[PDB]
Length: 448
Ligand SMILES: Cc1cnc(Nc2nc(C)cs2)c(OCc2ccccc2)c1
Ligand SMILES: OC[C@H]1O[C@H](O)[C@H](O)[C@@H](O)[C@@H]1O
Image (cartoon, rainbow, N blue to C red):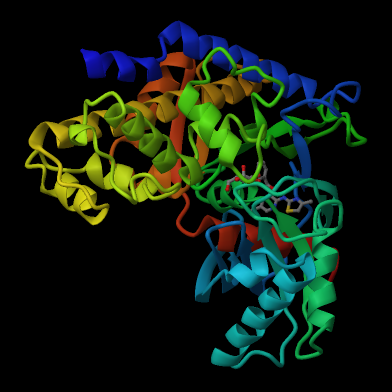
């Protein structure tokens, strides 16, 4: 109990999640009206991907994904069958992100990207061609059009200087001309939430949400255009990147924020920002555990009171440990080897506590997230017909796909909050690559 008292702190009651779900619905409406959109913590951003597409182009497209831990490049082909486009990644390649790119200027970052883009085109001899290029850019962007928009600010721990405030698609081109090595027609810039929804629509036409629970946490949904005041028009629907990770930045979570959350936030690349994301994201979960463990040893409840050298350095506890720990079959060998690598010698009950700590952190994350989705799905259900409103949600992100139980805890809780709704989850088999391509395919029936 002395331990379970400290852990029970991470608990959230059914009534707590409802309160969170209602507060999200609120910030959502606030960021959609013109009069509040500006200081709304949930920015609710028009993506310019719209309800009824005009028509699509076929052929190969070049897709970029940045915003992950890693930058990726892939070529995807696009065709047409009975029900809309089919897409399929045909070639691909990842490129680690250097420290000299993340510290330097936006200009340096993008040249590095320009390079990897040429390196890629080498290995597959294609440097001589000019294809439509879809860009999945996993950051808050204020779009002027499907291929126009500026970076509002970095999240997840990117710093590249003098990037905020500028057009991203521009900079991409800027860097390609700083090469002459090749040409590319940049036709669409989309959020990963959005890339993922689109990749999934073609599978299930009812797929109208894209949720990412990976290093960050964000969601996007199809909204009524008359509700999108920042964009002119009333017919049809535009996809809206909620950027809900910023939920709580106006202080809507304060009654739920634990000391471990205050500490993570303080030391983060962005104090006071992405507060909701820091309860859930992968950038942050392993760190929450680490802080919890360190609290537990400072109360002589763990590791005999003595914390490791690494256990004491920030970020030393990787989110992917939290998974491994929660995967241990019950024999404790999975948990032991982990703490072993971190310079500790866990007793048996040491291991059993660390399991409990993870479960406490990740399960909070699961539920906190479900409130958010639930509040989206409720909002959609509100401006829309009804009986049992079926709806599909396209999902992606390591935390969701790999953490052994987050998925189960998350589905259960979402459903508890959404009666009358029959929610279906699909995991995007390469949703970035093909979501972008699919969106470029239709953007490019205008720019080609
Ligand atoms: C594959 C796909 C790709 N693009 C779509 N729409 C797009 N609109 C613009 C301005 C660019 S691409 C699109 O619209 C259909 C749709 C998607 C999600 C919800 C409702 C309709 C589907
Ligand atoms: O990586 C998933 C999410 O991470 C962060 O919240 C980004 O701001 C958002 O654009 C993205 O969708």
